[PDB]
Image (cartoon, coloured by chain):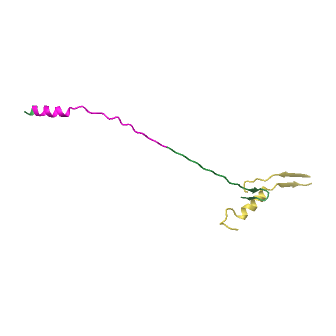
Chain colours: A green, B yellow
Amino acid sequence: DIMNAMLEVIGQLDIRRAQVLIEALIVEMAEGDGINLGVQWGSLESGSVI
Amino acid sequence: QYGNTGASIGNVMIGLEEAKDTTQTKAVNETTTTKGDYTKL
């Protein structure tokens, strides 16, 4: 009897395993900008600067 | 003179004097001329 029980357990734990295909998708979009403008001044004879 | 400001008049005037061209004379009649550094200014 115990044999016929454990064969019915083994029968149901022996099943095939499905297999998943995991496909990640990573999207990284960067963008940048900048505008740096300015006027400087100087006189080195008598040192005076902007 | 003030410390609030970016730079103080002392270091600026000292720097301007160090930047001037210095001359060193030895008479008897040698006279040499030399340009000063800007590193303090």
Q: Residue A2, position in %: x, y?
A: 9, 34
**Residue A8, x across and y down, in percent:** 14, 33
Dividing the picture into quarters, in which one does residue A42 lie? bottom right
Give the residue at the far right of this rendering: B28
Q: Name the residue: 85% across, 54% down.
A: B24
Q: Quadrant of residue B3?
A: bottom right
Give yes or no for residue A15 being in the magenta stretch. yes
- Tell me residue A28's x, y (percent): 48, 43
A7 over A44 or under it: above or below? above
Instruction: Return the residue found at the far bottom.
Output: B1
Decide whether the magenta segment is chiefly helix, strand or loop.
loop
Q: Is residue A19 positioned above or below A45 on the image? A: above
User: Which residue is located at x 13 percent, y 33 percent?
Assistant: A6
- The N terminus of chain A lies in which quarter of the figure? top left
Q: Is residue A33 left or right of residue A28?
A: right
Start-end of magenta stretch: A4-28
Q: Any magenta on residue A27?
A: yes
Image quadrant for the C terminus of chain A? bottom right
Task: Name the residue: 10% across, 31% down.
Answer: A4
